[PDB]
Image 1 (cartoon, rainbow, N blue to C red):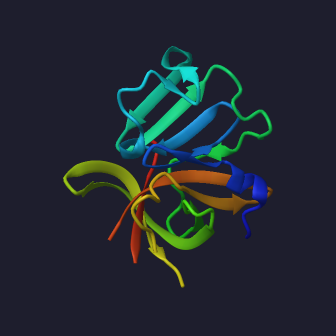
Image 2: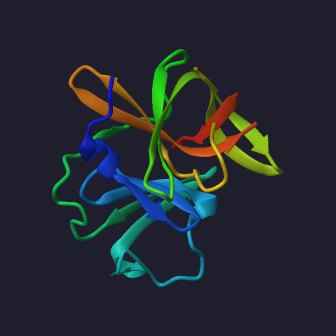
Length: 163
């Protein structure tokens, strides 16, 4: 399965990493890349954004359609163990680096001292600082599903997943 241009267009530079437009109003990212002490995101006041964060997973729901060109996709809490996902990595240069990953267990993990509710996976035939927030996706029938955001790596990578 090959990620089409529209799907890549959802991957958005954000803070010290990236985030992903799940739908016209819903944006997900990894908590530690989110700018702190700001009063707005994407030009919208914080008061107009419903924000939920836990275990390195951050979700924003805007009041205004921010990406009205997009269809809504399904966001799941991780994926079945053994699913081969693609991590849609954009680099600052603009290069697209889709990485195939075989996913393992959803678990509470501690990474550099902080609790991450996430899912591990093994890179198939790496990730670097700056890549956090990139989405983990897989195609199920007609639709692409997003199931985590990149959070950490050792061969093994971890995405944060929604609880």
